[PDB]
Length: 103
Length: 100
Ligand SMILES: N[C@@H](CCC(=O)N[C@@H](CS)C(=O)NCC(=O)O)C(=O)O
Ligand SMILES: N[C@@H](CCC(=O)N[C@@H](CS)C(=O)NCC(=O)O)C(=O)O
Ligand code: FES
Image 1 (cartoon, rainbow over the protein chains, first blue to last red):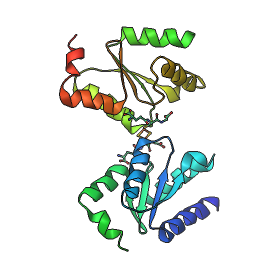
Image 2 (cartoon, helix red, strand yellow):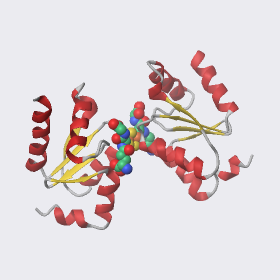
Image 3 (cartoon, each protein chain N blue to C red):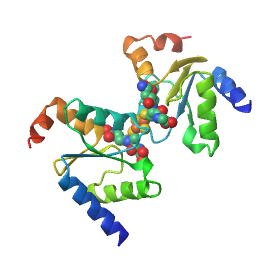
C-alpha cells in the first residue's frame, strides 16, 4: 500500500542521513532546530511538509504512526527519533547531541 | 475596509487581543502567559477564518507592520509578537498596563 511505502520511505531517510528534520517553513520552532544544527556545522536533511501539497499531511500522519509524535519539528539524529524541538534543545544543553553525532 | 473596523473595534473593546493560529506553539505560549496573569484574552484564530484569515493577516500588517503571528494587543496598544510579550513579562512591565 501507499501508506506502507510512505512508512518505508521514512525508515529509509532516517537510517541514511545523519539528521533528518520534518519541518514547516512558517514555523519558528522548526527554524530553531534547523538553526541549532547549523551552529554545529551539521547540515540536516530537511523535509518541509507544507511544500508537499496533499503529501505533507499524509507524512505527518505516517510519522505519527511510526513514532507517536504528530507535531513538527520531528527530528531524527543518526537513525534515532529525538523527536521534538524542546527535546532536541534539552538534549543539546545536556550536551549529549555533540556526542551521538559522532559518528 | 470592513477588516480595519473589525480590528479597531476588537482591540479597543478587549484588554488583551491575540491574533493567532491554532497550530502555533508561539501563539500557545502567549495565550498561556496571559492566563498565568489572570487575564482571559480574546483570541482570534486566523486559520479558523476561511479565506478571510489571510486577508486579516495582511490588514494587521498595514496597521502594525507585522506579518507574523502571534500579534498581541494590550489596552488598545500593539505590543507585537511572542518574545516581545515575553520580554515585558519577565521585566514586570506587563502587569503595569494590565493595572490600568
Ligand atoms: N513541544 C513541542 C511543540 C510541537 C508543536 O506543538 N508543534 C506545532 C507547531 S509549533 C504543531 O506541530 N502543530 C500542528 C501542525 O503544524 O501540524 C516541541 O517542542 O516540538
Ligand atoms: N519573533 C516572533 C516570531 C513570529 C513568527 O515568525 N511567527 C511565525 C509562526 S511561529 C509566522 O508568522 N509564520 C508565518 C505565518 O504564520 O503566516 C515572535 O516573537 O512572535
Ligand atoms: S508555527 Fe509558530 S512556533 Fe511552530
